Image (cartoon, rainbow over all chains, first blue to last red; front, side, top):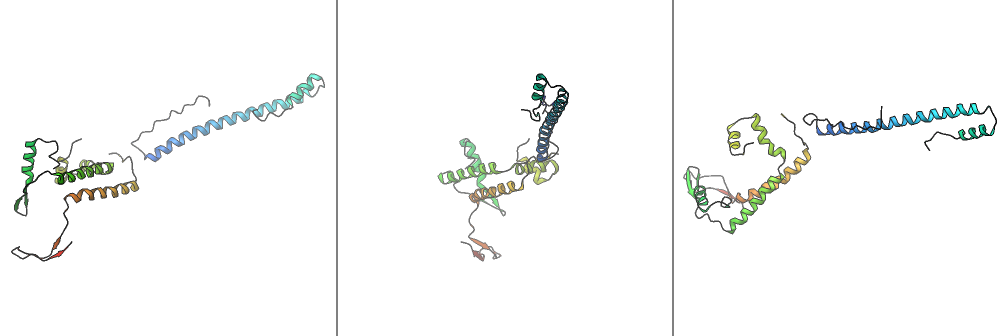
Length: 87
Length: 142
């Protein structure tokens, strides 16, 4: 839900049960799954933003095209750039 | 020799008196002149080194066997040997046969070192006795 407040605090693994290897594997899989989840959420929001801004650029260029003025052509030229990267 | 270290003169006197007397096959023999020279000092030094290396090499499995057996077995052997010892389920927290065998081999070398202090060299092996026990026929081992 919120990838900025990292809470890696799941340390509760008591030693009496399970062999040491399984304890280590459980800690490792927990950390790995946290990293994977945060990276996945980041990428999904990034691609949503890119898709939405590309759609808006398309619609706004289509609308500004209808008038051929200096201001309108200047705005279309600004929107003409591809926006499929963060940079 | 080992007991002589840091025990009073009279305490060592009493200990030497009691350790002198040996009973073996229903006859009693006494050691003449147990004297702590340098010749026994070398043996004491190697005994201390051998014991310390045994203690450092022995694994927690080796140490804890006695304690674990005492919790679930009872016998004259066990109660006797634990009376000789200090006083104080769950899984073993480290398990590795390869480490255990390497450690056991080194411990075998050390236990040979310690045994050679009391172990005399065999010179004859007996297979006969005259019924009066005056003579025997033996194989020479030298």
